[PDB]
Image 1 (tube, rainbow, N blue to C red):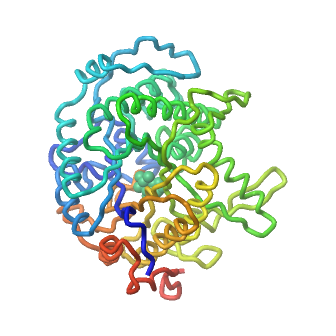
Image 2: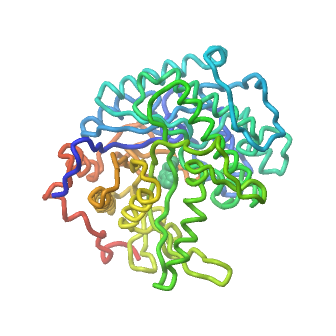
Image 3: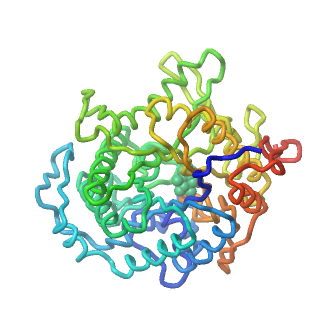
Length: 489
Ligand SMILES: OC[C@@H]1[C@@H](O)[C@H](O)[C@@H](O)c2[nH]cc[n+]21
């Protein structure tokens, strides 16, 4: 047996764009992502799969059924987001005291009069519907983390096709400080409207992926898919100060904890000669971002500066974790290696003989212990594991994947790390971005024709864990690597 603290909660995470649409009247055509996946040129290039989010699992209409299953499953925590585009589908008036030419947004004044003006422009049907969803959620005794942002922006803030084409005259997303200003107002506004229902807040989900895939990893088919080291830095600079202003905005309205959710890889040495390459990978991929929003340390242009407006803007850390990255020391610096981590073949084995998911991701649960303990020792801010899961429609590996990673969180707590819950990605299958519906991460299988939900055997395993607040003796064998012999190589 591995028992968790009495206050620890097992649950799930979900995104609006990925799960909401599918039922009559649920369509949200008004995001950069929606336009991006419907684009004929993007479809012909194979940048996006051709699957359309409006054919998705239908959480907007069917939320009481998702919640029914989560409750059957004994889940006690949920993290999801409000879709910005649903609240403000049309543009807001240009802000006052806003100089679009300044690099830094060090303050965004929001007062109650401003919020009531904001309220005039908000979609009321959507606001009421989200209230109905979150209320039903709370009525199941689910603790509620509200995330403000999980990738799609209102189209009036970002036209990604225009940007893909190299035209920077239109709405340019995280490349514009207007988006930073509006994000702060949006987040404060949502905290003002929902604080009675929320337990903890997150400002954003995985900002590094937004800037990294949007402007460098352009083969991934993430908007705007404009290849530029320089614009990726600008995007990341803007998203950081956006988080800080959102933190201040929410705090102006709420006393509740405000954190952030970030995408993590466990950086692993190829040989015992690559321990320094690991540290460098960790600097370049993790610490630089958290040192910015915790310690105010940031690079602006060429200068390494400290900004007092950034410092201390974090109460907790959402650890998203799927797999490792293997690195090796180089002449220049270091490189990530193909054949490990998320750079493997689908439904195969990594170069280390570890099985890979439907997405080509390597089974590596100890990475989670690595990540959780490293964050803890560096900052001493409590954590939630806000995502962890596997693309596995067959459910071959998920039972092992689940029990193994949950064991690693136990290990982390045992070492003294303050980790307060584990949130599987996800309750049910959903729209996996540029990959479409074929990447199935659900504990529950979705029939996309009928919108019926099915319990994969792993959902039954998760019920055993959640209802007992422990990995029980009877399932402890699943704290192991899925046997590789019977699987594809
Ligand atoms: O790919 C599975 C999931 C996505 O569906 C989520 O939207 C995103 O938060 C994320 N980051 C890493 C892995 N995942």
